[PDB]
Image: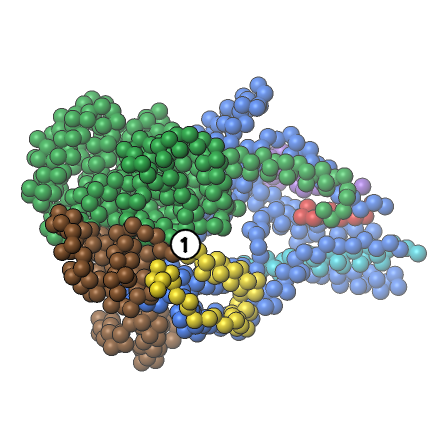
Chain colours: A green, B blue, C purple, D brown, E cyan, F red, G yellow
Amino acid sequence: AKTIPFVASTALGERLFAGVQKVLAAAKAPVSLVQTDAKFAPADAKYLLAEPLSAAATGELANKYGLSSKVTSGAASQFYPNSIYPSLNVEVVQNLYALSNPAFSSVTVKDESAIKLAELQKETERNISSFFRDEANKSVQATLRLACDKAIKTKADKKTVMVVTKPHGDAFDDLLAQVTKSESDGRADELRNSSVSVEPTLVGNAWPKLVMFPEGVNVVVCGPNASGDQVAQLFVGIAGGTGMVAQQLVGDAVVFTSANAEDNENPTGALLAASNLLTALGHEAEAKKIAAAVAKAYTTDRILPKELPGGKADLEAFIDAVAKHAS
Amino acid sequence: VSGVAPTIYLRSKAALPATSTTDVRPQLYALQRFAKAQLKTATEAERAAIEADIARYQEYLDSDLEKLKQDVAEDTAKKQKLIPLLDRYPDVPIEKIPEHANVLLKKIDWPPTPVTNVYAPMAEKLALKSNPELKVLFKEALLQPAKLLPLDVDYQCSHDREVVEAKRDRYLTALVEAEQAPPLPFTPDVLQLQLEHNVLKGELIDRLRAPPQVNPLNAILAQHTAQTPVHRSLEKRLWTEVRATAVSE
Amino acid sequence: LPRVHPALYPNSHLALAKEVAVLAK
Amino acid sequence: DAVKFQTLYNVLTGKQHLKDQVPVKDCNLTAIFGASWKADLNKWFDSEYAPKLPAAERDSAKKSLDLYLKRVDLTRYTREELTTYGILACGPGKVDALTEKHLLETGKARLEELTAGLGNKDEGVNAFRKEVEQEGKYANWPAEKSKALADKVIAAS
Amino acid sequence: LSPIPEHLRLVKNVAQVQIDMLKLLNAQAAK
Amino acid sequence: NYNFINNNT
Amino acid sequence: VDWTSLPAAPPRPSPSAPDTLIRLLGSVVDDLADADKVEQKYG
């Protein structure tokens, strides 16, 4: 039985540990979850599961495991009741260098001493700032390369569209524009083959597209500005609200997550996270079992949680229903 | 501004997120990764010193910064113990000096040396920011800011109300940042200034009792920066920022 | 040339810590 | 007439981008149109576009049109109000209840701010009524509805 | 000719600079 | 020499 | 008729900022007006 860690600094994370452990034991998989904390997680552990991270906790975890990007997955819109977005096969990607480093924004006379001192100081600052800029550009390159690989791996319908939010102005947006230019003008080959339509657009002209017709889009990319946080929250909600979407964090290692506010308790995002994790490790049959159990809970019994419209029920009873449907 | 708007632009200063946090762990991790990068260009001696430094930062992370807070508290304790000893002539305060100077000029009664007065201009800004009228407008603008901006013209001019809401939202942030901004643009290191004031006071009295204009101090810092690698210089920015929080909490 | 105190030197407290403990008592 | 409604159907279904770097929105569309948006759209649909084409495509298009209408009713809101102040975090079906909650809560907060800055609950309530009436007038909102909301917030305070 | 008055005026200027620094820090601390 | 040192200049 | 286009809104007269807001924000109103033009163009 493998020991996949499980970060949790809250009673929400604790009760979800208990529930998910019950589910996974009923599903009969050869792994076990280990209660830990975001600041004491064990390095050299590539595939992990987690709970709603705060911004600071995402920053810490990313700095630890070398993470670069956070992906979403709104598969639960099919299960949402009176679903306005059935089969929302798109993906949002948000960079993370702000949380991994929030402080990135930041000759009286010709005497030999003072000019020497200023030269040394500016050389030091040059080295530092050059390193930080190279790191930011590398993280952005990782995000864009991930989005391109994702759009390519998806079943290309001859469009394979990538929207890229780009409010002109700040340094993150400038870097992002530069990197889009670089990749598009550089590769062009898989691009023109799979017909991947890259598109830098503005927020006011992008988020209505995402809302009305996400059929015309497959991937979305955003930097770590307020705009990007807003678009990520938009998708996180539109997929069925905080709790229904399955988030993911990638880079040099994978950790799955479920978004949830203070008052929310829906664990379906975390169950889909567990399923994605098990598919990554190899237990695809168990992942399909879990997904079928979720679908049975939402369709046969239709036992919806309290926050959600329509029916209403508690977290633990919902997980009991999920486990009984699985086994 | 077509369409029956569902909501109204009501805002609360409590709802406006005003945290102004100062995180330490990500700054530390960035320092760690920077040292890891410099390791590749480092030679063997500096490679060893840098490995010790890296292990030190990992110890800090595993101990949850308490070791670093202890270390910076030790250094600041040394400093705060140092200054009152350099308080040479405390019974002779500083404003009483120009009186002595007037006395000596009266008693005694050439290329002069200039001075770079930086802290007097900032004193002029206090003559403005400390006014009561300037604070009254702050007290009365945030409570009713719609009076200032031409909202009626803006609503008629723009078909979409989202743009109008964004303009109003930015003005508050510009005002909130203005009132809470200090007279200074930077965070003054109080100890390193009281040090100079206590040493400089220790020099004028020795001069009152009784060529070039170069500052040999600059021919030392130019050597100190050369000796040290970069990660220690960045580490100073970390230790300084921790003195702000530890003194706050 | 002018004079400078060992406290106005950089990183002074490190080497002056002994005199401090001897003096502040 | 039929031209404008065909253009509208095309824009909703996404077969056409609007004639600039412009987004689709309830505001940025109904401003062009005569503010009889949904009623006349559905009417023209059920008259001239449903009987033409077969029944399978008819059902699919009816579904899609209802979805896109709900989506533009969702587009009515602002980005910041949607995300930051938590209107959508529960979901589209709960957007309405969350709007009501957000309105009453921010009303209470604004009331407390006015009373703390001024005191004199009569004066504060008067200034609050003026502010709400002006904001409704600005947002093209029924003044009677705004007055009812103001009295409601005061009674609930 | 003598450097005494110029030295004394240097002292006056530097002392006023230091007093202005002190007043700035005092007003900042008060705020 | 008679000049005075000022670290912040 | 071109419904797909957007109609010319009423003309915006000159800003004519107020002395109170200027005294509160000396060197920021220019930046804010430039950003307002940017937002009227894009956003």
Residue shown at 32%/26% (left/top)?
Answer: A45
Give the camera-side residue of A177 and B135.
Answer: A177
Residue shown at 24%/77% (left/top)?
Answer: D144
The kind of residue on which mark 1 rests is: Gln
Number of numbered labels in the structure image? 1
Give the camera-side residue of A18 and B113.
Answer: A18
Residue A103 at x, y percent in the picture: 48, 44
Density class for disc 1 (Cα within 10 Å; few <14, some 14-19, many ≥20) is few
Residue D105, compared with residue D137, is above or below; it is: above
Residue A102 vs residue A213: left or right? right
What is the quadrant of residue A49 in the picture?
top left
Residue B69 at x, y percent in the picture: 46, 39
Residue A243 vs residue A136: left or right? left
What is the quadrant of residue B131 in the picture?
bottom right
Give the camera-side residue of B103 and B177.
Answer: B177
Residue shown at 6%/43% (left/top)?
Answer: A301
Residue B72 vs residue A193: left or right? right
What is the quadrant of residue B183 in the picture?
bottom right
| Residue A229 in sight | yes
Residue shown at 81%/63% (left/top)?
Answer: B103
Residue D149 at x, y percent in the picture: 24, 72
Q: Secondary structure at mark 1?
A: loop
Residue A18, compared with residue G28, is above or below; it is: above
Residue behind mark 1 = D21
Q: Residue furthest right?
A: E1
| Residue A34 in sight | no
Q: Chain of mark 1?
A: D
> Where is the C terminus of chain A found, in terms of image quarters?
top left
Residue A266 at x, y percent in the picture: 19, 45
